[PDB]
Image 1 (tube, each protein chain N blue to C red):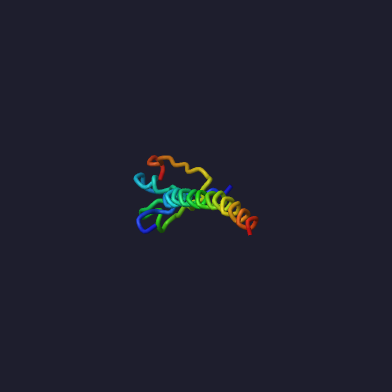
Image 2 (image 1 turned 90 degrees about the vertical axis):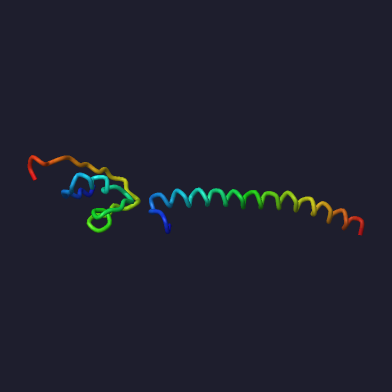
Length: 48
Length: 49
């Protein structure tokens, strides 16, 4: 169970998905197309 | 591929593969049925010979 962890802007949360484009999924973090995990994302404007 | 990402290109190519694989199954099944008919004719020709 590999748990990756980071922060991103809100209009780019849709780019954390298998096979996506845009300046996060191209070269910051690329999910494979053989994906079987679970992407969890929540707002943290009250902290970060 | 030239105009589409892999996640979606695998689905589109899999559809074409299934279609053309069905073409081959149709072709080979008919050759077996038709080869039995020419074989029956060759048996008649050998018998007359």
